[PDB]
Structures are given as C-alpha cells and as structure tokens.
Amino acid sequence: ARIAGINIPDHKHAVIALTSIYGVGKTRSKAILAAAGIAEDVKISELSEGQIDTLRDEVAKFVVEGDLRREISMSIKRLMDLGCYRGLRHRRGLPVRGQRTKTNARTRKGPRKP
Amino acid sequence: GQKVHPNGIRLGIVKPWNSTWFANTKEFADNLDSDFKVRQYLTKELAKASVSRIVIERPAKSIRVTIHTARPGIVIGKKGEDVEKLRKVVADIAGVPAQINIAEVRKPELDAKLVADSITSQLERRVMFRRAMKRAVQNAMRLGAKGIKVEVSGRLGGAEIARTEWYREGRVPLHTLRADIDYNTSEAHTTYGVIGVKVWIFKGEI
Amino acid sequence: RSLKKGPFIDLHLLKKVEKAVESGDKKPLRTWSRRSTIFPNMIGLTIAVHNGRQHVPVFVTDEMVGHKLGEFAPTRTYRGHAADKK
Amino acid sequence: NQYYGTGRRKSSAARVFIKPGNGKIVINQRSLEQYFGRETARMVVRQPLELVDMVEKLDLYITVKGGGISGQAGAIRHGITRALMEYDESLRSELRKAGFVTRDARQVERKKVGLRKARRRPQFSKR
Amino acid sequence: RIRIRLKAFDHRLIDQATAEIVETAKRTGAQVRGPIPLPTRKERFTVLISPHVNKDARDQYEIRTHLRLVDIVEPTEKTVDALMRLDLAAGVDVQISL
Amino acid sequence: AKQSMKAREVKRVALADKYFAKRAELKAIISDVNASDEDRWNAVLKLQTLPRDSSPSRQRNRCRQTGRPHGFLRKFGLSRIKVREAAMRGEIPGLKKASW
Amino acid sequence: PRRRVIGQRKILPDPKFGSELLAKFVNILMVDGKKSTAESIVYSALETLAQRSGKSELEAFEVALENVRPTVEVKSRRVGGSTYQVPVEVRPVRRNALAMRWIVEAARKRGDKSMALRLANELSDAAENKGTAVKKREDVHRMAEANKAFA
RNA sequence: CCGGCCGGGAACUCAAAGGAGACUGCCAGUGAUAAACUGGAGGAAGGUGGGGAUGACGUCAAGUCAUCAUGGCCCUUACGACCAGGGCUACACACGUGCUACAAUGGCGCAUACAAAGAGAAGCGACCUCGCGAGAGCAAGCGGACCUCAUAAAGUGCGUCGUAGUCCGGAUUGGAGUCUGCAACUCGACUCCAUGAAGUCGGAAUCGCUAGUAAUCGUGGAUCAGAAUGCCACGGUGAAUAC
RNA sequence: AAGAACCUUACCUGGUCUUGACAUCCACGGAAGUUUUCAGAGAUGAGAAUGUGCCUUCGGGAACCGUGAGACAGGUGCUGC
C-alpha cells in the first residue's frame, strides 16, 4: 500500500493497482491474485490490511522496480561494453530488433531532426 | 495486338483441345513435358513435310498421336518406313508405347498453319508479301471461305522501321463465339529479322 | 532464440580452434564463418571474422560466449553521413 | 394433410412444414424464441401471418442450413411464402400486394481483380 | 459390392462414356443403382497476363472436373468381367473399388 | 537463358535426391529428441560434412522451360507465361477462361 | 445522374409499429452493420424518453422533430465567379431526413459518458426544444435572413 | 447408446447434367396514325432480368533484347564458368501505398450460437497425452459430399471497466522459449513474461463508391523448407444519397 | 518479384578453370557405379576400398565416365525508336 517507489493507488482494482509497480503487469498481477486468493474486482482501499501485509512479501517473491531498473540498465551497459552490433544500435538510439530505419521506426529513432 | 486470341475463348466451345487426356496431379507435369517434347521433335523433323496440327491423346498410359498434315506421303515416307522410327523415338519420351494415326487435310489451303508456313516459305525466298497476302486471300475466296483476315508485321522487304499491315475479306465475327473460325500466329525469319504472320480464317457460321 | 538442441559451429572452425588452442596463441585466424557460435575455449583469440570486404580481428572475451561470430563483424558501413548543419 | 414449402435466401436453403391444429412453431428441434425469435427482426417471419390469423390455427416445423442469421431468417420468410401454395391465389392476392413472394436473390458479387471488394480502388494518386 | 467413381474434364465428353458403361452394365446383368451426378470441382486460377509489370491486369481460368458414381450391387462374374478391360473411354479416368 | 544456372539447378536436383531422402533421417529423426545425446554431435558433424547443396530447401524450383524462378506454378512446372501460351494453344485440357 | 429521376429505396418499417420514419432514423445511425445494437439503443432511448415526457414514444419524438424541423437552407448556385450562397425552401421529404441527420450530428457531438447517455440527453433537450438541433436550425436561419435578401 | 446413430425412404433439400422461363410477349395511355417510350398487370424476375468474360479503327515512334525468340553490334584465357562470405533488408531526409489506433453505438471477463468457398499423399495430418503458450509425443482417417486443415468472427446475453492518454491503443525495448530450415547475427515467423511510444478523429489539399454497393467482420488459398498488413478468392452483418 | 535467411543473384569481395557448367564432332582410355578417409572456408585437390552391367560383329560394340584437338559453346553484355 506504500511499497516500492510510492505505490499509492486508489479506486483501482487489485490487478490494475499492482500494475503501477515497474516490472509487473496484468497477467503477473493476476497470478498474484490467484496465489493470495484475492478477487480481481476488489478495491485497494477496501481490501484488508493484513491481506496487504501478505501482499508485500508475496510480490517480494518477484523482483520489481529499482532492482529490475538497474538490472536492465546493467544489461544494456553490458551490450554497449561488448561492442556488439545490438549495443551499437543502442548507442545510436536506432532500433535493434531489425525494424527498418529507412522510413519508419521513428519512435525509437526520436523526433525528426529537420 | 493485345486483342484476345480467338482459339482460347472457344476451347470450351467449338475448339476441342489438341491434346485430350486426363492425368493425376502427380504425373500431369511430366506428361506435359513429354507432350512439349514430342511436339517439338515432330515439329522439327516434319517441318518440311507441312504438318498442319498434331492431336495428342494418351489412353491407358500409352500415347496415340493423330497427325493432320497437308502431304501425308512425304510424312509417311516410302511404305511407312519412317512411321515405325517415329514411334520408337517418340515412345522413349512418351512413357511407352507410341501409337500414331495419319490423317490428310482435304483442303490444305484453308488451314491456317499450312497457309502461314507457306507464306514463310515464300518470305525466305525474298518473295513480296504484298503478293503473298493477295495470293492467300485468292485461294481462300476460290474455296468459298466465309471470311478471312490476313495480317503481318515486321521489317517488310528491308524497311528499317517495323510496320503492320493486313487485308480482311468477308464476314469476320470474332466476338461471336458461335463462329467457326480457325486462327494461327507463325513467325517468319528473314535476313532483316523476324516477321510475324497472323492468319484468321472464318470457315462457317457454326 | 534459435537451435533448441545443439549450439551450432561449422566443423572446420571447431577443429581450427581446437588445434589453435593446443598449439598456443600465435596469430589471428582467417575464418569466413559468421555462422558459428562462440564457445568457452575460444576466449583470448583474435580470430578475424569476414565482414564481406575483408576480415576484421575481434579479440574474444568470456563475456561473449552465447552470441555468434557475425554480429561482432558489422558488415554495412554508414560512417555517419553528411551532417550538413546550417 | 401436411403442407410444405422450401425457399432459399442468400446461399442458405430453408425447408418449411406447416399443419392445421396445433399453433406452436419449432425450428431445428429448437424453440421459436431461443433460436431467432428472441433476437431482433423476430416478428418478420410472422409478418405475412399478421395480415391473417395465426395463433392456434397452424403450426410449423422448419429446418434450415447455410448462411448467417438474417439469411436463414429470410429463408424462413421465403419458405413460408412458398409454403402458402395450397391456399395459392387466395393468399397470393394480398400477400403479393405486400410483396414477400419476390425471390429477392441479390447474391453477393465476386471480388474484381485489382479492386478490394469488387469496387474500391487502391487509392489512386494524381502523380 | 462394387463402387466405381469415374472422372473426366468435359461433361459432354463424359456423358456418352457414362451411357456406354451403364449400357455395358445393363447387358451384363445390370443390378445398377443409377449413376450419381456428384458435385463438380472447379479449380480457380488467376495468372498475370503481361510478361512484365501491369500488376492490375490478370487473367482468370478454371478447370472443371466432372465425376460420376456408378454403384453396382451384384458381385456377378459377368459384371466383374464387363468392368474389366471394356472401360475404354480415352481421357476418362475410372476408379473401381469394392 | 543462363544454361549454366539450369544445369546447376538440375545438378542440385539429381545430387539432392541422391543424398537426402535416403540418409536424411540423420537430421530428420536423430537430431530430434531421442536417447542419443553423445551420438547427435557426431551426427550434426556429419551433417556439415555433407556439401552445402543437396537440401531441397535450396531448390528455387525453376521453370522447366525458361528456367525463370518467378511466376512458377508447381501444379504444372511451367512458368505462368508458358503455361498461358500453351493454354491459348489448347495444350492443357479444360483450361478455358473463367467467367462466373 | 444526368437523366434518371429514380426514387428512394424501400426500407423496412419498425417491428413494433409502422413508423418507417424512425426506421430511417435507425438507418442513419447504424455503423459497421450493427443493426440490432443500433435498434436496441433506439428502443432503450425511446423508453428512457417516454417515461420522462409522459407521452408515448412516437408522439414524444413527433413533438421534438417538429420543433427541430428545418425551415430553409443556403446552398451554392448561380455563381458570379465570386461565389455566394443561395437560400431556398427545403423539400418536405428532405425536411425530416435532414432533421434526423442534424439529430445524429448533435448526438455525435459533445461527450458525457455512454453513447446512450448522449442520445438520451439530445432527445431530452429536444423535448423542451432548446437543444443542439434547434441550435443548428436557428443558426441556419442566421446563415439566411441576412442572406434572405438574395433571391 | 436422443447423434440420421442405425434399420428404413428417395419424401424433401442438396447435388449436378439436360430443358422451360422475360420476348416490350399481353393491357392502357402517350408518341408524327412511325419507331419508341411511360404506367399497369400477371409474373420468381420487366425493360441490357443481376453479374462476368469478350478491347473496333487506331494512337501513345507507350513498356519489355532481363520470360522467350530475334537482325546486327560487343567479349570469348573473359563482357564466360564454379565456390565461400557479403549484399540486394544499408539511413540527416522526401514521396506513394496498406494495417492497428485515438475508444464506453466501446474495451475487457465468462457463457452462447450462426457460414461460404478452398486445400491435402516427400502431404493434410483427428482423438488422446504433455505444455499458460506457441508447440512436442503418439497417431486413426483422408486422394477425399466420408477424414484433416477446420472452433468462423462481428454477433447474442449478462458481468465489469465510470471518460482518463484511461482495464483505449499497441509501438518500442529487455528477458524466457517454440518450430522451420545445413543455416533465424546480419535478415524468419510465432509464443510467453516484462514495457505501454506517439496519438484526444487529423489542415491546405485529396480519393473511392448508387445495393447485397459503401461500411464492418472473419475464412481460405496460390507463392512456399520457413516466413503476408501484399495478391487472389469466399462468405457473415449490412447503410446513406441522388434536388 | 504467386513470397532476396542461404538457394535465387543478374551484384560485391576473395579463392578458383580456360573446348570450358551445359550441346554437337573426333581420337585415346576406362563400365558406369559404389562406400570410405584426408588437406582445404568451400568448390576443388590428394587418396582408399569397391564394381566391371547391358547383344553380338562376342577383334566389335552400345550406354555411362575421364584426358586431348580445334570447329564451336556461352553472355541477365549493348541496341524495344
């Protein structure tokens, strides 16, 4: 209810409330509810404080926000250190998967220069 | 020149296929190959013999080749001595054996391929196409052919620029599918280059 | 991400690298195979991979094993361009 | 004696039996309501019968196949119009006055080459 | 006992062969069901007309294939002999079965 | 029309039937999961020992006349233009223009 | 077309009662061929309306339509090369049709929550005829009047 | 054994072949008593019944010598032939064309139905078993009106999401896998976990389309070892406008 | 272009052969074919086992394969005005 960076949802349903944390989305949060037994429709505010206390170590079973941040950033830092073509595309800001740079992939390319 | 080929649209109508045989999807490919092969062989070997057309059939995994020709004697040779060889050679690519059935065209001047091959045999002799066309039209009308449209295109007696020319006579209802109209397109090699000869021949109303 | 069973190397490269290891590091290898996969034993080698115009020497480090030879020999060269800043 | 009609709306084929006495309608063992009569255009099949009496006077056993919902519904409609044949001109007077007797074939056209659904152009540009 | 299913391209070309085999059957003991017309397979085709580009212009084709069931019930010797090597019909593929 | 390419193609046809479809299981079965972990290494090593060709997937399946890779029809084997030229000449039974 | 004066298509009358007019409203509303849903929103709206008006659905719409019903409209014609609008009287057949188009127009405009809520709001505003449809009507009168001098 | 499942019937659909039917043929009026038109009737259908195929004279010295063929020219120890790797997919940009969007006539959850037309033997490959999943193991049946791809989806009902860049959207990226194929880095697709970009219905300008049409939904193919938002085809729902 | 991962490919780099990858002509040899090993990125290159079939003229042949000669082969090389 206060965990992570902040995690103070209100009016949100249990799964969408949990989604706010970096590193956890819909299906994982549904797995958390299938584990705790909590219903999807319950409000975060009406839900029992002790069930939140179980919720804390429950979602602590899966690494989330900052550790995942520094993990992914350390991975990208790794790719850059390898000098791999992928890491070069990470340095250019250009796509890595294989998207066409000739016209599209503007999103990863950033705003148009001229 | 992009206009529809008259035979193709009447193949289900008044123009039965020159090769009538069913096959399974597996061997149909190879049988078409062999068909093209025997048609080439018979085309080359009998070119001077003026064969008009070759009607392939393939009953019971064995080929039977009807042959419509202007001059059956020059095709058969002396008392059939060529025919047997033609059956052996063809049979080898035909899947074995090769039956053959000769047939003479009673009025060879009417038939298109014979006319075109004649006109090509004239063109190689440096004969003037302006005469050839009128000669073909003359024989067609003397036989009472209901219609005709001769056309040619190419260098035309050494002219540097290729040019088309034609001369129709009689009723020529290409749009009427009821119509009995033979047709051919045959290329004629010359010193200045290839000269296509197209020949429409309207034989009858049905 | 590919090859469920069996990491892939072309046999001539695994034999050249085998007798390259047992004989001590001396000179870069002339391999054209971008298709192979780095293995643990290949580390420390300066083996030159074909970028299509020539061979570029790459010094193999254990930090790169699961990867392949190709992507460390970038083929197409786009330098930067002409910036043409005004 | 039992009466019959067929009809066929948009590649679908209907088959319609009708008899005196009972008034209930049954289509493919399913209830008149549960199959289509609770969905919209429920009353259309009865629309010709609204001009006359229906309630207990006649019952229908219908089977249909092919097409979608509205296609099988119009097939039921054409099938009722064809099943009124025993009362022929007697019903065809007012019935044709209201139509429904019309085949109304209006089959879908085939896609034309280079045209997305037999008309649409590939967004022609001036240049 | 016997289930024959013959096939050919042209309907008009397969009809007289159907008449000849049904007649060959009637004279050989008959016990014939009555031939079934069957649905006709129609392979659609659409090939590019031009040697190069002209992507908008294509040419349609189809190859109708008519089929016919025969269905003779009797395992009569006269029947099985008549169904053997009297089929003829060039261009018409017969398929016997039991 | 690039005869060396057609002879190369048919050489892949002959040689390709000659090797695989016979020894092909060495990858088609053995490389698939089974109780032969040690052997599968020597298996794939023989797989690369085979020439780069012989595999059917390397067959572009060229036309039997012009040899053109594109516009091919597996149902015939002829290129679209040549099966159409044969069609208009009446070579292929029942290949009339369709209008429905 | 240049010549044909062919008439309108025959739409189906409303299943509960023979108001083909509102059936034409259901036509000018259907999107993506969702006929049954469009019809269901129509009945749901007419029910939500009639209970509040106290009137029967059809007549409650009749005294909403009549109020929003267009009088005259401007259209380009007889240009001097400088182009200017020509006001003219509407054909009665085009009258209620163009009115229902203005109803749907006002419906698509603005947002609240549900489309059934927007529709109910537009019909409610049409009941005491102070809505966006009479607004567009009086606006068309403003586009005229000063243009009405032309003839 | 409530499944046409099987006796049983060719009854009816369906399925094809082969015929009839619509021709301004009939009625009325108009029309120069002309042809012809308008209206009506019956009729399944009324005016070319609906659709499709079929491209005149010719033009553009249109495109194609790179389908093929061809007159000449040119190379013929290379302007020929074989192999490995690379590239044809490169990116400061601009244009054309398609797809998913920007949402609660909606999204999402459960339940619940209703098609047509194609394809399959070096192949289509049920069922069961395993796996959230893509798929794996085994594998009946099918040259097909039987069996398989192969459960249509939009829809229908209820349930919730309560108008925000939002349970919209799905881009991008990171990680974990599947299958194909020698080979998935360059440069496949698909799946799962994570991530949730721009975008609030789009200006000047501009396009298509008159009925089973536009709109919208999904299905199948050929190409093919694998890989469609493309192409070709199929059906489901289904408008408005014509002064 | 009814589907560029290799293949395709016409392209680039490098390694390769010059009667040639394929077709016809002749001499001079081997059946063809077969499985297996090494060097090489591979094609190629060097081997090793193995086979010696098909009518008669059985002194020959023919089919297939290899070396040699030149005539030729080949070209997605240019010219659609």
Image (cartoon, coloured by chain):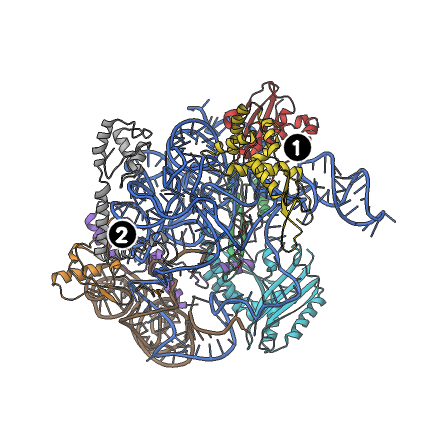
Chain colours: B cyan, C orange, D red, E green, F purple, G yellow, H blue, I brown
Residue under disc 1 on the same chain as residue under disc 2: no
Expressed as whole percent of the image width and height from the top left, the position of residue C6 reads 23, 51
In-front residue for pair C35/G129: G129
Which disc is residue E17 wearing?
none
Q: Please, is residue A17 above or below residue F21 in the view?
A: above
Q: Name the residue under label 2.
A: F26
Q: Please, is residue D126 above or below residue A7 in the view?
A: below
Q: How many marks?
A: 2
Hey, what amino acid is under mark 2? Answer: Leu
Expressed as whole percent of the image width and height from the top left, the position of residue B15 reads 61, 56
In-front residue for pair G26/G82: G82
| Left or right, B138 with reference to E94 | right
Hey, what amino acid is under mark 1? Answer: Gly
| Left or right, F22 with reference to H114 | left
Which disc is residue D99 wearing?
1
Expressed as whole percent of the image width and height from the top left, the position of residue H104 reads 45, 35
**Disc 1 element:** loop
Question: Mark 1 falls within which chain?
Answer: D
Q: Residue at x 24, y 51 (%)?
A: A76
